[PDB]
Length: 49
Length: 49
Image 1 (cartoon, rainbow over the protein chains, first blue to last red):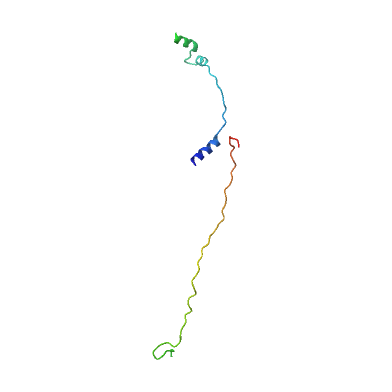
Image 2: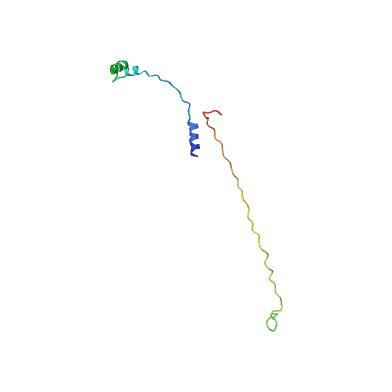
């Protein structure tokens, strides 16, 4: 009975979701930060040398 | 005067009209009006028939 209760609420409250894609460029994101920003390529190459 | 013999024995045979037989007692099934379940509007599932 408990499983049937679970199944009923699942079918009744199920929803087809909106499926979205978001692309994030880390160089752009780090450069556009308000307070503590930096440049990805410059800091990456500096840290390797 | 009381229709007895010299010894006091009665001279007329009496009667009492024997009680009228046993009695039959019966039981019976009793039924009453009974209703049925109702139907509500149905939900729309997300899956096909």
